Image 1 (tube, rainbow, N blue to C red):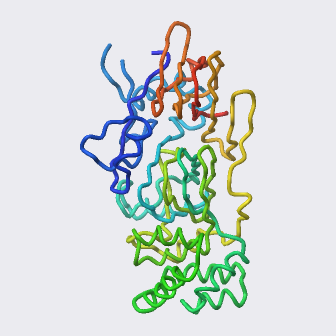
Image 2: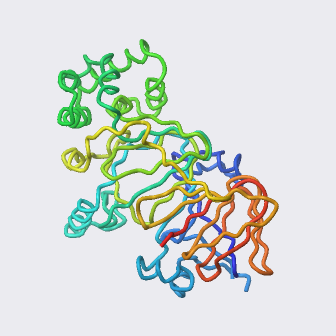
Image 3: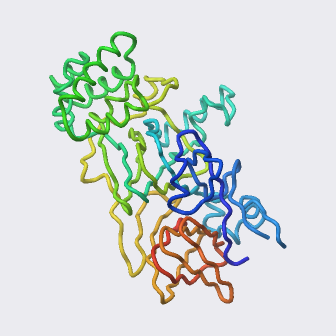
Length: 392
């Protein structure tokens, strides 16, 4: 009861890997389903579970019944529920380019969709919270992604070989500024019919005459999205490969995409998503442009710089909703404590948690819920444990 081993949901979305969770963590998949996301938290659709008495209960249900005790008063008063959802993501194919609206615009979209009466669960629901809902991603295997606009002159260099693909490209090259970058982003997304095929032919041709990145990433993408205007997006947006242990915060109003690999992600039970390419779904382009900041982000500023204090490696996050830390285990115990509920996930090695008399082993890929009332616990072993919690 002090420390609770989690039973977690695996979402079998069609883009998931049939093997990654099995290779990494020994998770059984004899039916060979795609295993896209492993969920750690209290999502009302698919809450993690804990064991009673013998029986299991929804973690969400348990929290709901003893909110202050399990969450801590700070989190109870501030959020009224577990304020994060923690995932393992296994992208076996590239996923869609996404933008998260800011606070003001999330309020409006949420309100606009509510006024129009669209169910929260509908596929047309882009806005599920009136707050900006940020994400952090942390690489467990090499993790290929796109994030934010590149420096204007990086984009200039990259578009020259495809200058003939669309007049909007030549227009940007003439004066590579925010206004024309915005115009280019929208024009590419709005290409239709022979205008679209002409542009994609110019791009293909370039895949044969240009070597290295981001051309290679485009090739990887095109296997899954051969007829998507988003094939141009790596020329506009930074392409990053995170090494295992590196992390990146996804800011509002900023196009990004997870392209390949396995990562931890921290987010919330509610999310706001505007799609921006690599999708066969409908894009409201005006609305998208209205929710994007066309401001370059230097590649040097993409990764989150963590802070090491003793055994703890904190990844400072500029919101209160959640915090994220990595803890290096040793054979001598170290105390891990927080004012909030916490979830601890064994990244590698093996962790032995202790609270008083209770002992709990986590092998890689396993997790435990620690209620606010049960902090601190002692951790020993080898490898590393990841913690999601609240610093409030």
